[PDB]
Amino acid sequence: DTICIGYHANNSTDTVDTVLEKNVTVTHSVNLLEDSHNGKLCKLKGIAPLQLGKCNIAGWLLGNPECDLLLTASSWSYIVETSNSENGTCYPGDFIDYEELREQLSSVSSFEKFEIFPKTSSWPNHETTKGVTAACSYAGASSFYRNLLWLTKKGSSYPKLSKSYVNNKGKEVLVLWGVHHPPTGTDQQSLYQNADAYVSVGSSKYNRRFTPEIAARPKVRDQAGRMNYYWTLLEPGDTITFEATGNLIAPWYAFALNRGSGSGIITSDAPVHDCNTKCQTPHGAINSSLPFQNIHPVTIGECPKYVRSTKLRMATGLRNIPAR
Amino acid sequence: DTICIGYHANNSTDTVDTVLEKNVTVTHSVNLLEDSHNGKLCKLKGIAPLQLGKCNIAGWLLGNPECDLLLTASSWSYIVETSNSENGTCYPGDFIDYEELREQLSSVSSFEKFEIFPKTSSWPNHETTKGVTAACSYAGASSFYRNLLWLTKKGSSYPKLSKSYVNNKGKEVLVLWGVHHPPTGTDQQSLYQNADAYVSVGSSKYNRRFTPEIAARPKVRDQAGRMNYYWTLLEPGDTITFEATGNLIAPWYAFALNRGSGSGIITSDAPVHDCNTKCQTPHGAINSSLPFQNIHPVTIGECPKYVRSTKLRMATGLRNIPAR
Amino acid sequence: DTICIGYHANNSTDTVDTVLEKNVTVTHSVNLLEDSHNGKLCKLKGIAPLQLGKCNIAGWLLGNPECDLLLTASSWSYIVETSNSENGTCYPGDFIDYEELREQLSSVSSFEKFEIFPKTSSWPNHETTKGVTAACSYAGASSFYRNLLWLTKKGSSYPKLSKSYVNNKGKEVLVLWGVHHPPTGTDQQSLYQNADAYVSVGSSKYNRRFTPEIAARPKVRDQAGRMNYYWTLLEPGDTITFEATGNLIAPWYAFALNRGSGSGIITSDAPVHDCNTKCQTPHGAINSSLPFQNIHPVTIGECPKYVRSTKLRMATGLRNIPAR
Amino acid sequence: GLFGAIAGFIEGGWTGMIDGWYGYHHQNEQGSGYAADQKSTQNAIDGITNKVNSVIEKMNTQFTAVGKEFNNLERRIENLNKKVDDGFLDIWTYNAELLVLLENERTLDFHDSNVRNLYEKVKSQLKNNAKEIGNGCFEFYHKCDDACMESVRNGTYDYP
Amino acid sequence: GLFGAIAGFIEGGWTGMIDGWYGYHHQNEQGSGYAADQKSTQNAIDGITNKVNSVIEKMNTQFTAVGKEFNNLERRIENLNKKVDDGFLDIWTYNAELLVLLENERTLDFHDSNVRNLYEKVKSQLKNNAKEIGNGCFEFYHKCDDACMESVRNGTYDYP
Amino acid sequence: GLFGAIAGFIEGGWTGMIDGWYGYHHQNEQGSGYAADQKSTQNAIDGITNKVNSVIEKMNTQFTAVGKEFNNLERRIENLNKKVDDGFLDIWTYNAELLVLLENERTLDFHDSNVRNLYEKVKSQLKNNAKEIGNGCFEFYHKCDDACMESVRNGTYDYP
Ligand SMILES: CC(=O)N[C@@H]1[C@@H](O)[C@H](O)[C@@H](CO)O[C@@H]1O
Ligand SMILES: CC(=O)N[C@@H]1[C@@H](O)[C@H](O)[C@@H](CO)O[C@@H]1O
Ligand SMILES: CC(=O)N[C@@H]1[C@@H](O)[C@H](O)[C@@H](CO)O[C@@H]1O
Ligand SMILES: CC(=O)N[C@@H]1[C@@H](O)[C@H](O)[C@@H](CO)O[C@@H]1O
Ligand SMILES: CC(=O)N[C@@H]1[C@@H](O)[C@H](O)[C@@H](CO)O[C@@H]1O
Ligand SMILES: CC(=O)N[C@@H]1[C@@H](O)[C@H](O)[C@@H](CO)O[C@@H]1O
Ligand SMILES: CC(=O)N[C@@H]1[C@@H](O)[C@H](O)[C@@H](CO)O[C@@H]1O
Ligand SMILES: CC(=O)N[C@@H]1[C@@H](O)[C@H](O)[C@@H](CO)O[C@@H]1O
Ligand SMILES: CC(=O)N[C@@H]1[C@@H](O)[C@H](O)[C@@H](CO)O[C@@H]1O
Ligand SMILES: CC(=O)N[C@@H]1[C@@H](O)[C@H](O)[C@@H](CO)O[C@H]1O
Ligand SMILES: CC(=O)N[C@@H]1[C@@H](O)[C@H](O)[C@@H](CO)O[C@H]1O
């Protein structure tokens, strides 16, 4: 009669590493590293993302012609640009503080678009129609942005305009506008008459004045002229006031912003589907409860910690010695 | 006859955690986490802090009326703003590079205030008195900043002024000044005469020129006009030179700065007392030799490392088994 | 007859530390901390560094007189400034976005210098010679930068010039230029005639216009006048176009840049030698395979991890008990 | 083995026993068999489980983290941002990989210790009534039955 | 217990002994009592003390650290600064909490090992002159006095 | 010693033995001598070597890293950059110093365990044929020769 003391063992082939020895087979273990994904851009908490497709933030907000699809959008869980998001500023120029605008948009979950300055109403004495170019063509004909209005002299009569708006929305209002810089002094005449005009925007915290800088510059999309775009967030109660005498690409539509958190802009060419997730990445959605992941550093939602590791297996059982 | 080998034990109720088991009672242990404080803003190395109370850095340096208490101050261990530090720029406008000025002040331990351009002396041909407004009222009447001088035309006669100063202090000199922007062309007349005047400051490293930007802006503290404030550190030896023809809110008092380290600006509503400490935080002063603290990330002096932990107890004794 | 079980031991005097005890002598150990160096600035992968000696980045690129030695250079492994690199902007003024230029240069491994606008060819109607000052003297006489040309009125006749260049190099072209600001209106006359002239540079992404700001400023190197330097990287294909009517310090030589990685600018007074290394630091070159070093945080090449440690010895053998 | 038991004086494991990690064999007249010790196996399990949960706790989950954009004149700032992102990434990777490496070593030794402790818990019970052979087996002198084997794999036994 | 002694083959502790952490009991004609072993207890103390000092050393004290301000057009930069501050805070918290957790485990095992080592230091002295009972107690065969007990809790003894 | 062997029940080391870290003495008629055990010594070596390589692996080498410059109106940004650099430096220094400190403790204990395990690997071979004296030496009863000593420092022996 005898009795022996021993320990479990099996056919397991999982291996872990230790400081003293590599590739040790153990009886049981757990993986802490998630490396698999959805392959698709999904919904976060029911709401779906906002594709810009061929458009970029600039195009979308400004109202570039090709981005009419986006016109109807009002809420999203995260904004998505792609490898071919080049439809934005159709008429050459500069978008002052563009990056800071994007950063602002990263904490906006939804807004309400509204005609701040009605085309046919807020502009008598000044001529509304006939403010288009080939640079921003449509269907084949010439056109312009759907949110900005190009005011030109009404029969060699460009009086000094002064329009204002009061923020009565209880939210923040995003106001965008532009300033034109014709190539030759001749054109200044034919567009706003007055040889030396000016534009002046102002509110409680904002104050800035612009003056045309006519000159000779290379052609971009068949244009030696330029156009700088601007923006600012009008606070609740405050009043913004434009006052120009030519060159003022005026605000036609504005947005009342809803600040939400945990949203953001991403660049991905992955297909959008009717799928819901708790963690999204540019490569696809993730669904794990593991502590780490090596899929992508860019994240939206609640994800595992990004890490460069290839393998992270933690032993639980003991050294597996079959000795069969 | 027998003999036994055993280990100490007692009534201790302190518990520590381990990777394998939680809440284990041990015989002896030490706490490494400091979580108690003074509740008061104290002195650091004898010197007391500088309260701004109802004032902010802008008010203090500019000389806003309500901040007369601060006029006598010259040295401090750290600057203190509160929840009601709104007395600064009384006359609407902008304070160019304000944040950078604050950053500079964070390494200043003391200075010497001195009338750089005496009110009655450096300004003949130009009229000193009568440069006040209701925006910066005092006792009920209208007034202005105590360190800046508002020069206005001396009987429709505003000649081209040109004043200079040489830094003979062996230190750095902080020079502050402003530029006024009247609302209507009419006022430009009534204030400095000349319809189109200008201001031009310059030194060895500094060079900039300003021009009035008259326009129509909402009323702030009953004012449609504006005033931009500026500053620069004049190096030892160099010379700063103002040259204006109207709109120049001139430098009346300046400061010679003493650079000290380990100082800074903080926001706190904690009472200041005659107490000395080696470590101060916005919640109060700390007096510990423990390695960590979870009181506040903001620190002045020599403190423990801020951490989010709730508990950090390290075992020293052994597993306590009373078995009474 | 007997037999005993024991362990090695010796005369070793190396000591390591442990959490429970300090200074324990062991039989064998390895040092992980490298603390020795070359003391010399060496070559990295065959190529030698570029000394600026008495010059700085500004001097070198602009072509300051004293930096003629550098004129012949075209490739380097890393740029080197010293404690006396003060020969740069000889004629007082400002170098807009200077730091960003340096950052750009940090990823440039070589370039091709080329006369973009030939002195005697691209400038008829305008007078080339006679654009020198004492501020930038040479051999004793007055002179100017070798890459920039000072254009002055050709017999009270300063016509409106307009020159252009097309980037046909397949690389990036660094274009530098300046704008002069005379002290008195009188000098404006004697230099470019026209009382109110202007300068206007422009390309596809660049667009800016300058205007002289004449005034009174202290003397620097016997000069109350100023001169601002500018730069921009012209993309492949694009065209840059200058158009001025006076005050334009014109581009004479430009550079086609070769982007390389792992290069950079450093400050050191260590002697350059004909030595090759894989890791360079301002104190000298390092040659080790150890994981850490406490020589210098600044590094070029492939080095150990900088650390503040004084000692890092890891035990390998056992506690050494001679018991002789 | 730090404790000399597993893959030590007890050469190998029993692919047979499947009730836990540690147990007994037993060869009494009435027949053979295997039986895992709950006492032991359950404690090891509770510990290891607690360890894995503790490791996952210290690694807070990551929330939204998107990139930032910079214009062609914000290079220094762009790289500073780049330096920060890469720096944190290096550290977390290092921490994660190291913790696992170090804790794995600790786990394997834990088991080795557990096995060794059971052996000596039995050995101190028997004493004279049996003799130590090899591979951690004891040979009974007073040849005992199944009713007795259950007093061994229980701690009762009794017989100095 | 990783070493099977504390809360192991020596079931509990003596609320009585108060001279140190490890000691002896002893029951000789002349009477009973408790006596801690300086040799053992002092070493454990020196070690533990050295450990606690080493842990506090690696944590350099924090010097002045105040916030920074940003205007409404420096959002990216404001957040970069925010990202940095939070990132360092996560890491230090993680390091502090983990070091304590890991070292606590190591400390408890240290004591367990110390106790076990003392037991076997005595056991190898006696040998035949006494027999191993339970709870780490030895029963003398040659019944010895207080003058002898002091040769045991000393290492002198001598009597194969 | 966590395992009571080195600088423990085996008081000191043999400045003589130079074939490895662990070995045997032996005093047979034919003469004395020292002989290290390859089995033991080689394993310790392989481990320790693996440890040192693993520690160096986790520390990726540093590539180019030069400073940045800021104008007198970029102070906040200059300090942010300063905060970042110092922050990373503190952490790496802490990590490096701590890993070494902790692993050193682990290495010394490794050896102690190795020694203790060899002792008991021999002790279980002899048994009755010799008696345990001191300093980990065994005294033969059946006095054996050099041909026999080689069956001991080999594991063959055989003689319950
Ligand atoms: C190159 C490497 O990673 N080494 C190991 C190898 O030694 C082992 O035999 C195999 C299976 O466990 O896994 C890995 O290939
Ligand atoms: C409305 C507008 O901006 N037109 C352009 C179009 O000409 C171009 O082909 C496309 C992609 O390059 O971007 C925009 O859609
Ligand atoms: C001179 C000045 O700007 N001080 C203002 C004061 O006018 C105002 O009444 C008070 C309430 O907001 O704030 C500050 O004390
Ligand atoms: C003392 C004075 O000038 N009155 C103003 C008052 O009109 C205003 O409502 C308040 C808050 O902005 O600040 C000041 O108290
Ligand atoms: C300091 C000391 O003990 N000297 C000897 C040295 O002469 C010899 O070369 C070495 C190896 O044989 O061992 C010791 O280092
Ligand atoms: C070899 C070495 O590092 N010297 C130290 C010595 O400075 C220190 O005073 C002593 C006790 O702490 O230990 C070592 O002898
Ligand atoms: C060509 C030029 O810029 N001249 C100066 C020179 O006068 C001065 O002595 C030197 C150092 O002080 O720096 C520059 O070389
Ligand atoms: C843990 C357990 O099952 N206890 C019982 C014990 O009470 C009983 O005396 C013995 C034989 O009857 O069997 C078991 O050991
Ligand atoms: C530590 C010490 O004081 N040593 C002595 C010891 O030598 C002696 O055998 C014993 C009994 O007389 O008394 C003391 O314990
Ligand atoms: C004479 C001249 O050229 N001006 C300065 C001079 O004040 C200084 O002594 C010299 C040598 O360092 O450096 C020059 O820049
Ligand atoms: C840079 C240096 O001096 N280090 C030398 C290297 O030149 C040499 O090629 C190599 C060959 O073993 O040995 C290194 O120590």
Image (spheres, coloured by chain):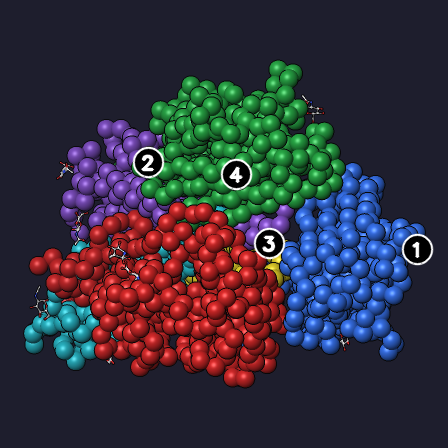
Chain colours: A blue, B green, C red, D yellow, E purple, F cyan
Q: Is residue B139 above or below residue C52?
A: above
Say which chain tag 4 marks: B
Q: Can residue C290 be seen in this view?
A: no
| Mark 3 closeness class: few <14, some 14–19, many ≥20 residues within 10 Å | many
Q: Seen from this angle, which residue lies furthest top?
A: B139
Which residue matches tag 1?
A120
Which residue matches tag 2?
B168
Which residue matches tag 3?
E76
Tell me which corner region of the image, top left, top right, bottom left or bottom right, holds residue C40. bottom left
Q: What residue type is labelled 2?
A: Asn
- The dot on residue B138 is none
Residue D4 placement, left or right of A76: left
Q: Distance between the residues labelled 4 and 2?
A: 26 Å
Q: Is residue E138 above or below residue C112?
A: above
| Mark 1 closeness class: few <14, some 14–19, many ≥20 residues within 10 Å | few
Q: Which amino acid does label 3 sit on?
A: Arg
